[PDB]
Image: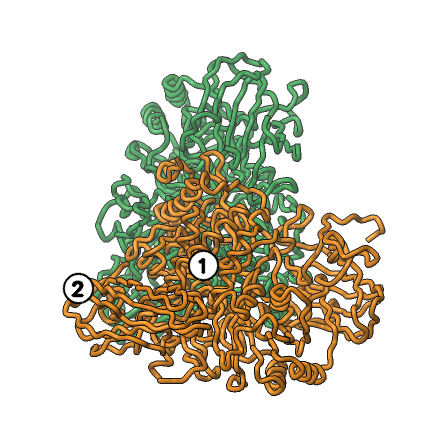
Chain colours: A orange, B green
Amino acid sequence: KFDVEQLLSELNQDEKISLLSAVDFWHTKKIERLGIPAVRVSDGPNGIRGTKFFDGVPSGCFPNGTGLASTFDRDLLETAGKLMAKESIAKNAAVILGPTTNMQRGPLGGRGFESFSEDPYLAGMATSSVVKGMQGEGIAATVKHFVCNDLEDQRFSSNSIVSERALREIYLEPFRLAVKHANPVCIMTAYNKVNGEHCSQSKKLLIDILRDEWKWDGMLMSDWFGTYTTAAAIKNGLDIEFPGPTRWRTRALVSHSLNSREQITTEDVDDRVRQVLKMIKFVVDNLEKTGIVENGPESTSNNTKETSDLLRKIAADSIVLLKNKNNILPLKKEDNIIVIGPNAKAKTSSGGGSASMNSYYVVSPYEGIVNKLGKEVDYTVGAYSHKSIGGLAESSLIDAAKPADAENSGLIAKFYSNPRSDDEEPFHVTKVNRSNVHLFKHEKVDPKNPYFFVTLTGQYVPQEDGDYIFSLQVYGSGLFYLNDELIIDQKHNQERGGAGTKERTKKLTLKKGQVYNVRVEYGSGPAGGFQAGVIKAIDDDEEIRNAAELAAKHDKAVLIIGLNGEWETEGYDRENMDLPKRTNELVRAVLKANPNTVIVNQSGTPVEFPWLEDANALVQAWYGGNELGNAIADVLYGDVVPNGKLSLSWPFKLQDNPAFLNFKTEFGRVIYGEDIFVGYRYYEKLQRKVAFPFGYGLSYTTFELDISDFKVTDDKIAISVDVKNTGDKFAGSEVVQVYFSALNSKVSRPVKELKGFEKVHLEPGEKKTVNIDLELKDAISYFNEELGKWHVEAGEYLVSVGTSSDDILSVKEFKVEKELYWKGL
Amino acid sequence: KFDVEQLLSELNQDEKISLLSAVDFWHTKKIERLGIPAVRVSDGPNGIRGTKFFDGVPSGCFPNGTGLASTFDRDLLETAGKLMAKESIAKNAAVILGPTTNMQRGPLGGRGFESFSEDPYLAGMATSSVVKGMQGEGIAATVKHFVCNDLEDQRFSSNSIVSERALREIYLEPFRLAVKHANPVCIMTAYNKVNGEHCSQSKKLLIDILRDEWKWDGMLMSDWFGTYTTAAAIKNGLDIEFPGPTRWRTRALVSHSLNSREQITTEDVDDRVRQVLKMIKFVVDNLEKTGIVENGPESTSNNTKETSDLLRKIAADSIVLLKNKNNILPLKKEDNIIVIGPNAKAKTSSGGGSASMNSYYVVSPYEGIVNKLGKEVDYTVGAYSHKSIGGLAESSLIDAAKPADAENSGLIAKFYSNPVPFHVTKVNRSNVHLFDFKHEKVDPKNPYFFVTLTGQYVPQEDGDYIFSLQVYGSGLFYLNDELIIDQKHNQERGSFCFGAGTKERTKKLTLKKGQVYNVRVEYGSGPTSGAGGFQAGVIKAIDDDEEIRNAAELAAKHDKAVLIIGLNGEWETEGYDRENMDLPKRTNELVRAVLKANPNTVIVNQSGTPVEFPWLEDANALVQAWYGGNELGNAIADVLYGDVVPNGKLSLSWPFKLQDNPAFLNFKTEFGRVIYGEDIFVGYRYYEKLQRKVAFPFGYGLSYTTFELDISDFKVTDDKIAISVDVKNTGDKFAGSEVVQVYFSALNSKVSRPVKELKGFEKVHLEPGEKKTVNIDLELKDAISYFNEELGKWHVEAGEYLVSVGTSSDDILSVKEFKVEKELYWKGL
Ligand SMILES: OC[C@H]1O[C@@H](O)[C@H](O)[C@@H](O)[C@@H]1O
Ligand SMILES: OC[C@H]1O[C@@H](O)[C@H](O)[C@@H](O)[C@@H]1O
């Protein structure tokens, strides 16, 4: 018993106002007097960070959305969201800030890795599965970012200018599917504008569509700081401003607007408060099922074998095999192999930003291979591809003459009020594990005028002789000292490189075995952050040469390449679709030296493979979460048979893509020039060849399918597809994909549209039948912009059933006589 | 060598934003780096209160605006300007929040008293004159409130709905006249809306009209808290938010708006900042001439004879003699008088609100007469008419074991952060006004504190005493540590604190003459149940029926009775409007009784706006004094006795009955709106068009001498009208001033006009038999235009016009016609 209307009747005006914003970054407002508790929310869509970045409680990191979507497996995505709920309860977060489902209208989007698919049906069913899995556990979902936050560049002001047809068919559509099938408890409004109006105060989006048309009854929260007005946001449907303390909705701003008849009425305030109360009721109603403790502690209690195995399956099923000539794959355990490449020993579990977290652990691909084979594995780096140098904390000690324990590994961070007599004391001390230090709450730290200083210390011991490059990045100020000798100055002259500085570096000749003193004196942000790193310097030409040489001296090479969460991050978009640095040269040399090299690529979004024609085996890993390396091993050796399909089009070159010319905010606007033609919708219409198309992925076995039954009423389509593993060696899963085409429509349309899919597991020689039933209106409508309505048009239509958007294997023609106009769900 | 553009180029973005709001109730932002000092500003339009209300430095209270305009004396008004400036310097206020020129479309307006006149011409010229005086002495004026802040009711939300023609002709006009002749340094935007949009964010008012059309380059400040958006107020031309600390213009609100492309660009901000820079430049460029000292102290250095001379004079010339049958006046020293009435011994210097201040002294009328004759004068109170009961601090002592001295005369006030001491201040005024109470240990954003109020009280009489408590916050009143008055439990809504505080709660007790009693008031400030305030008071109860009789009989045994009546600054105040035009309580019944027993009585009324005199027909001598400021009593004497020959003329129409007024049915905010239904027909323009008779018509007042005039030269050119008027004091006993008023009529206009409109005036002082000539020059377009709403331009229409020269709107003595051959349409100034 938490009663929304009786509480609305009992709250005073000031309490009403106080419910319309969050208290701090993660919490709503407790109202002891009426039994209304504070609710914790937490990022993000691929696992749960909890209440802090710096010194964060470790957690279960899932694979990233585009990887998730590539499973084409609702049941699994549903399991995944169920796991995300357990991870959340472990952090005592009653509400998750995920899934994310904006749209990769082009490939360069900085958060492209974080959403699901360029296809609105796949995005919407992925979204709907994850939310259903979260909410079945009684943890609330927050679908974000509503809507058209499809690039990062200047997102707070960016105006997405988009027709009502593209808006309905591509960008609103995954939210519609999620609402219709999963009823999320919350939605987060976007930072941007749509057609001139910030989403967070758009009556069209937040009220006309979400409320009047869809009848969705959940709670809208702003993206963080993504509120832009006092009264209009309240009038126009933004239920709660995050984070607190409130900027736009103080008691004085709000009640002054009420008393002065400016814009809003008490009815507007109530309407927003009611919606907050309903989200609160969902949380309180599930407290018995979840065990959430208000302002409770955060643990690593979900860090179990059950969780590890599941994160492993999810990661392995995300992987997409893109090429496999000559049976390079699977590898045999007895193959003589070398592992090469910049991503080989990296732990690229996620993209950057709010979706990232602190992990229990991350298994590198190298380690995955080591674990697989149960012994040492030859290795060479081949080339570097980092955006900035980190790795200092990850390879440092407090006192070198003590063993590399967990208690002794890392750096000590000592916080100070002043930068001081011998006798000032640290007001906080933390063991620092990761080099990038992100800021953070303390009583000696003034909330929004936060001035403090960090003394970061430890010992670094070189494992090889030669040159080593040290680095510092600060937002604020700091100085780097090695053996109490200044080596890098980020105090005196500063250059912006997005709020903070450019990396400054110092190359130094060091000696294997010897203990050097690392001390970094940092100055608080005027809330801040910094990164002191170190990397062993290499001779790039010689290292390419070496990797080539080594590759020639082994049967097989495994080259692990790609991008990382610094190249793909909330905050900015990519400049280009290139792999970094000398990667491409590394790859050319290795392919020349051993043509039977398997290439495994980790990225959230497409990259150009210029050497593609010479690459005989190519695997798309994605960013795999905690178990990424094990999952990769599973696929390479065939303990998992690759079963993922691309959730994205993979064009040859950046210029081929439909958003090539409009993927930048210029004069504050982004024109959606391609209209409905996004992803494969674009490339099939132009008949432009791509490297790999939507829905593509190979297996180690072969499959065949046909429509084995088909029926249409005036209202419905039922289709039965027979699928069979025609191989005699591997069991495996195939993804049946159902596309619709209009054969004689008055209106321009995509060549075909995904409207169904089923994933089916088959032992060698096994045959199964999957059923796919849809209401016509789901399958064949388009949005009629002039009439302001969806339209099931009379005509002839074709269903195409296949294993990719290209690989169509069975079709059926049918007729539609019953025309229908509609709105809503 | 303060260079507006150099500074604007130099300020960083956070410095820019910090300029767009004030730091506290009274100061702008110091930018030390750039030698931009904190400008102090101060209320009000009739005297300079200074930086605090409670425990405030005493000042020179001028008479209230309707009084001032009644002088019809530009020179004298310009002189009061200078005096106001000098009083401003004494307080280290570089900027004055005045003059006030909203418009008495009806008589009931809470701040009716504060403005000048229902006449756009009179109010414009009074405004211009007062402003010229102020700014010749280098102190900046702030003409307020722009615009249509014409009742008090719900004024933060009130939507003044008014045609463009009325807007232009009546409400905007006095601002137009002030900008045109006087160029005030600042203007203050009104709290209210005009046709659906809050003044403080109306592009139409603040930019299209004020900037684009009039070309005025001053700075716009908000009324206090009257900002309602972050970005739209910045974009639509509101230069600075008052008071600090900012609500709508925090560095975060503004810079988030800018960075998120929400509504405002950096241009808009520059544009605001710039105007602010100019106001500051004015102040800086006059620091030598004025000697103002940034965050300076507050002195009473101007409490001087010279200054008192002038207040006495300005007060004297504001008085309007309305009736004088049978030569009851001037009173003669040898006359046997008794002074009677509710306002005889009271000190009603001003109207209520931000116009008020702490005075050096107020000479009551009773005292004024005492001073003139120099002997005890017989008196009886006659009746009470206070709205609420005060007095308690005034007539009390810290220790009963001491004499009635300076620092023993008051109560002690102690301030705690917990209920029952950061500050201790000795209190002499019963109204404890905490609105701008500042303190190191008080949060301006949340002013949470308590007051214990203490001292002892000694009654000079035997009977019932009525005690009173009034609060905004919470209060408890104990006499002798016994609970007598409860303002904690079940509060009601009444008129205290601009209508926000409590109804008066009182306790009748029996007391003993000379007996010491203990007074303890325990007060919680506003946040505990704006900082707020409270009032504890006491008054001697009277037999109300007997007290009338007593006065009536006493009046009968004297040659002449002097009956002092009217309102005061609790009946008439910022914050709410009057409910009716009635004299308070048993006042009328006193006058009916006194008039019947002694037909030789002079009534002196004090009000800022009209009241009904239902016994008008029986009163033979009737004088209107307004609210006279410090020298109010001495000025009443001067005119009563003929040392000043009454010379004021009414700034307002004075109808017989409230129902008679144009705004009878729409002088209340309803559904957040006020429909200005009478359109241009405001004041005399209403009455003359309806041929409705009034008790006393606009521009009316008597003398103790007689006058005649005629037009002795009349010339028309293309742009100008020259008129000459010969005026003679045709009496033989008294020297005096007559006011020549010049009105205009359109005779065959295509458009409904008023019967005539005030367009020029002159005051001329004439010894018995003296004749003089006065010369009025006016530009044609400014005399005879109406606003053509359809074309959105002023129109000088072809046809015939009539000029009426008279000594009131109802006493035309001479006329002249001219023809206008060719029309002109025009905008601007
Ligand atoms: O980190 C909290 C939130 O902040 C914003 O930066 C992001 O756009 C959201 O996706 C995220 O949930
Ligand atoms: O004191 C500052 C301001 O206070 C407000 O209450 C009044 O409306 C203004 O006229 C005055 O100048």
Q: Earlier in the sequence, mark 1 or mark 2?
A: 1
Within the image, what quadrant is residue B714 found in?
bottom left
Task: Please tell me which residue lies in front, B11 or A709.
Answer: A709
> What amino acid does circle 2 point to?
Thr
Which residue occupies the extreme left position in the image? A817
Q: Which residue is mark 1?
A: A99
Query: Quadrant location of the C terminus of chain B?
Result: bottom left
Q: Position of residue B168 (x, y in %)?
A: 34, 61
Q: Is residue B252 above or below residue A816?
A: above
Task: Name the one closer to the observer, B108 or B348.
Answer: B108
Q: Amino acid at mark 1?
A: Pro
Chain under callout 1: A
Q: Nearer the viewer, residue A704 or B431?
A: A704
**Residue A584 visible here:** yes
Let me know if residue B765 appears in the view.
no
SS at badge 2: loop
> The numbered mark 2 sits on a residue in which chain?
A
Who's the residue at 33% across and 68% down the image?
A723
Label 2 crowd (10 A; few <14 / some 14-19 / many >=20): few
Q: Which mark is residue A797?
A: none
